[PDB]
Length: 207
Image 1 (tube, one colour):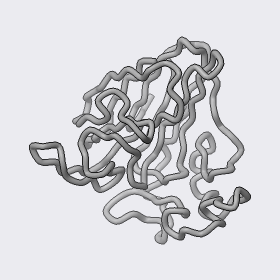
Image 2 (tube, helix red, strand yellow):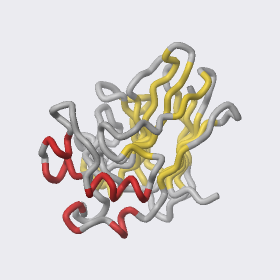
Image 3 (spheres, helix red, strand yellow):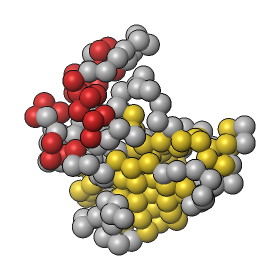
Image 4 (spheres, rainbow, N blue to C red):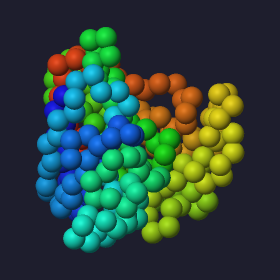
């Protein structure tokens, strides 16, 4: 599938794309306000994610640090990023279908729309002002809203026993973005799309 990644924020984002053990396409790219990056993701890819990184500082070698979503200090990500990160998640061509979602399980940093380019399925969006409303204990330094698992590292929030339920903190995200995962065992908000589908991920969507 083709993904057009578009930054409509007033600020630069450093887009990232990975399946956890490898880059997708070039893995990362600086997108100043108004810029776009079109990537190819191999058909059949499972566990792919796209996210924004904010306030990055890179040297000539593409090494440095980002305030949110840092992936081992690299411009071109090969691994997933440090929370808080709003996540566009996808597995492609699993038995003839694509499966997409947005997740707040690793927190929220940038508002996001994740939409198919086809009429065959719907998009999802999480663009509420989660950072401005973020409870003090979840606030990430300088920007973003951490998930409770990141902050507290207990089974209640991280769902490590394999059994967990909603919490005051998951509900915070869920009420602001009902169509995004708010904890690991949230009722799925995954959208099923045709296998031929391409996508657009928009940071700071408007219309």
